[PDB]
Image 1 (tube, protein in one colour):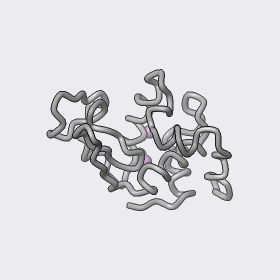
Image 2 (cartoon, helix red, strand yellow):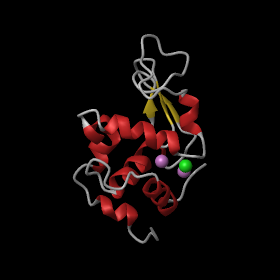
Image 3 (cartoon, helix red, strand yellow):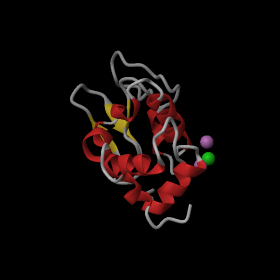
Image 4 (cartoon, protein in one colour):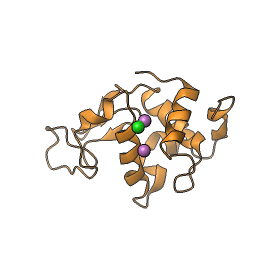
Length: 129
Ligand SMILES: [Cl-]
Ligand SMILES: [Pt+2]
Ligand SMILES: [Pt+2]
């Protein structure tokens, strides 16, 4: 499922990401834009042999079990396949443990390089929330 900008914002807001640990909704949407281009089915192989999964490109080295990442953790206690659902509940729930880790949204390189310090609330601009 490829979300719409304001569709995704609404869904994330409905799941409690707006201002979660201080990160306004715009950050979470901008993160999704530059991670998966809003596509729940996005997958991408990392250099280390891990894979990034879903709307926020959650990664198999620490966060989920994909059955093929040697010496990884499943800190969110889910199959990585669960992050490719058209229902974003597990992507959001796992992002909430990721973002609490102490690194914040810096865990996402896309957010750090493309969203951090930008007018991120442009990404929610015009949406009925
Ligand atoms: Cl839900
Ligand atoms: Pt929820
Ligand atoms: Pt939902």
